[PDB]
Amino acid sequence: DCAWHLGELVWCT
Amino acid sequence: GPSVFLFPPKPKDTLMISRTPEVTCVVVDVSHEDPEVKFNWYVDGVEVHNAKTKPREEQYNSTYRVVSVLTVLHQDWLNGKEYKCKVSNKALPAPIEKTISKAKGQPREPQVYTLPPSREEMTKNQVSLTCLVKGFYPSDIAVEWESNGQPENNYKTTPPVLDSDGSFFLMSKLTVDKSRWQQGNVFSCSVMHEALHNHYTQKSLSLS
Amino acid sequence: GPSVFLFPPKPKDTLEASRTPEVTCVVVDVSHEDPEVKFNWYVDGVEVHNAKTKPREEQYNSTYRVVSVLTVLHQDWLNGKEYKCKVSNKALPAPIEKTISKAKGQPREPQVYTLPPSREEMTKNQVSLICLVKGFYPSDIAVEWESNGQPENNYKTTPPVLDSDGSFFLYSKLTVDKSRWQQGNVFSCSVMHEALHNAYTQKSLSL
Ligand SMILES: *[C@@H]1O[C@H](CO[C@@H]2O[C@@H](C)[C@@H](O)[C@@H](O)[C@@H]2O)[C@@H](O[C@@H]2O[C@H](CO)[C@@H](O[C@@H]3O[C@H](CO[C@H]4O[C@H](CO)[C@@H](O)[C@H](O)[C@@H]4O[C@@H]4O[C@H](CO)[C@@H](O[C@@H]5O[C@H](CO)[C@H](O)[C@H](O)[C@H]5O)[C@H](O)[C@H]4NC(C)=O)[C@@H](O)[C@H](O[C@H]4O[C@H](CO)[C@@H](O)[C@H](O)[C@@H]4O)[C@@H]3O)[C@H](O)[C@H]2NC(C)=O)[C@H](O)[C@H]1NC(C)=O
Ligand SMILES: *[C@@H]1O[C@H](CO[C@@H]2O[C@@H](C)[C@@H](O)[C@@H](O)[C@@H]2O)[C@@H](O[C@@H]2O[C@H](CO)[C@@H](O[C@@H]3O[C@H](CO[C@H]4O[C@H](CO)[C@@H](O)[C@H](O)[C@@H]4O[C@@H]4O[C@H](CO)[C@@H](O[C@@H]5O[C@H](CO)[C@H](O)[C@H](O)[C@H]5O)[C@H](O)[C@H]4NC(C)=O)[C@@H](O)[C@H](O[C@H]4O[C@H](CO)[C@@H](O)[C@H](O)[C@@H]4O)[C@@H]3O)[C@H](O)[C@H]2NC(C)=O)[C@H](O)[C@H]1NC(C)=O
């Protein structure tokens, strides 16, 4: 999956 | 004579894939007669070249301030690679060297727990919502607050405290007007750290 | 030349009328060739003569550590009097002077709020019990935990942060075994600060 921070991409594994 | 100071990337930059982390090798007390500097950067003993010299700043105590920035990959840093800056200047009988790197030690997942105000704070005008981050290594972390997609800025965070298992812990606290807490509103605590799934976790808090 | 450091008394020492709170003038980098050091103390510019000199100590780096300690009255320091140590020594151009006192400004009463362990944590061996201390000025304080008249010592406490109302706040975190917590036990948070009723207060926490 992917994590978003304030609609800014954080990380994807 | 001249002096060297080597600073690490911001925790955020190493953790947000979409940001750009960089080491910064600062050189202070730099003379007018020989302002020129040489930088050689080495990654794990091995030289690199994509260094850059940010523009020379005049200090107004008659010294110059010359700075070298090296860009670095997220994963190189997070895997504990070592970055050495070497500085050479005519007014410096021997070159100076400095190394930095991520603190050596097995990484540990932070445990994140949100905490409603005391039945006792309820009288007072403004209330404190707490985020507790415990059991994390290493100490490089970022904590942010928000509600309805939107940053809340009245928070404050403690410097990471060393625990007795060797991990770190901190508390982050946010102050809101009471009524808002009453008004059913939902607040989120955002934690970015390496030993987390996708370097990011979030936790919410509300009335019950 | 030689260097000077003047330290405050420990906060607890000032807040317990049981102890003796003391100010400390510390002088490092004192030479072997000339280790003799004149101290003069003043409490608000007014000289005093009852400071007491600690045993000389060799630091093993061509230097002595020379100390002078001054006993203070609780009220005296509490009412922010200004304590000053003039240090003098033949290997120093002019005497060095330093001053300290209580951090100036209106004292404010701390609020102490205990916070129980989050349900999410309840699946672990150990649980974190929290003591929120906010709303105090100045930042001089001491924090302890207890249970059944017994000191529980497995806690850590953050250093005070400066809050945005000019006040300070910190957290103490006692970690105990889940079992103990479930079994309805009473854990207490002890706080000593000038601005409390009798410079002491105590909250407690249980399932
Ligand atoms: C002439 O003046 C200069 C300039 O100094 C300024 O102006 C003067 C006149 C005064 O007003 C000063 O107050 C001003 O700073 C003098 O230069 C100073 O020299 C000092 C030693 O000679 C040196 O001391 C060291 O400070 C370190 C902390 O540096 C921080 O913090 C200070 C203030 O706290 C700040 O002013 C500095 O700029 C610096 O800020 C950091 O910048 C870094 C790197 O750029 C940032 O990180 C990067 O950020 C970018 C984007 O911004 C990006 O995100 C990257 O990812 C990232 O890398 C970072 O955010 C800032 N860091 C921090 C922590 O905030 C101390 O750590 C250090 O301690 C070490 O050494 C000590 C003893 O030597 C020990 O106590 C200790 O154990 C450590 O080993 C140093 O003490 C000053 O930094 C320096 N000031 C500046 C501005 O450069 C000069 O000396 C004087 N000349 C003469 C002849 O007298
Ligand atoms: C030869 O060596 C000596 C000794 O060094 C030690 O031994 C050698 C062999 C080495 O192994 C070292 O590693 C050892 O430290 C050198 O002496 C040192 O000089 C330094 C500067 O020259 C000096 O640094 C300054 O320290 C301040 C903090 O001092 C604290 O904490 C340090 C370490 O945390 C500790 O070393 C000090 O002793 C002192 O500890 C406090 O003691 C006071 C008084 O004893 C306590 O208060 C009292 O407590 C009693 C209980 O007994 C009672 O309750 C009383 O009521 C109360 O008054 C207090 O509780 C202690 N606190 C703590 C936390 O322990 C720094 O803050 C300071 O920096 C500040 O000043 C500068 C501004 O000008 C700024 O740069 C800076 O940002 C700050 O504002 C200094 O850095 C060292 O303290 C000193 N070490 C000792 C032990 O004295 C010597 O220089 C060297 N000579 C040569 C030629 O090489």
Image (cartoon, coloured by chain):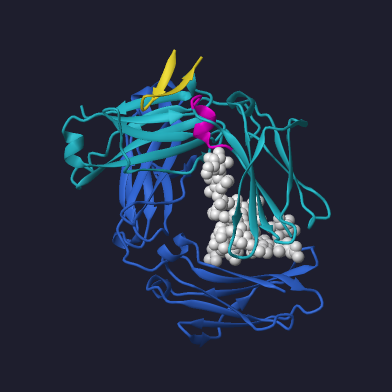
Chain colours: A yellow, B cyan, C blue
| Closer-to-camera residue (B49/C41) | B49
Q: Quadrant of the C terminus of chain C?
A: top left
Q: In this view, does C22 lie above or below B147?
A: below
Residue B191 image offset from top left, x and y in percent: 43, 30
- Whether the magenta-drawn stretch holds residue B15 is answered as yes
Residue at image point 49% right, 68% down: C21
Q: How many marks?
A: 0
**Which residue extends farthest top?**
A1
Side of C80 relative to B118 (left or right): right
| Quadrant (top left/top right/bottom left/bottom right) for the N terminus of chain C | bottom right
Per the rendered image, the range of residues in magenta is B9-18
Q: Position of residue B66 (x, y in %)?
A: 65, 50
Which residue corresponds to the image point at 34% horizontal and 67% vertical from the top-left?
C105
Picture residue at 32% right of the left edge, 41% below the top = B153
Q: Quadrant of residue C73?
A: bottom left
**Residue C63 falls in which quadrant of the image?**
bottom right
Q: Nearer the viewer, residue B145 or C204?
A: B145
Residue B126 in sight in this render: yes
- Residue plotted at (55% across, 26% down): B108
In this orientation, which residue lies closer to the viewer: B133 or B93?
Answer: B93
Q: Where is residue B83 in the image (x, y as percent from the top left)?
A: 69, 35
- The quarter of the picture where residue C180 lies is top left
Q: For residue B50: magenta?
A: no
Report whether residue C16 is seen. no
Looking at the image, is B136 positioned above or below residue A2?
below
* Residue B102 locus on image (x, y percent): 63, 33
- Relative placement, left or right, of C198 versus B119 is right
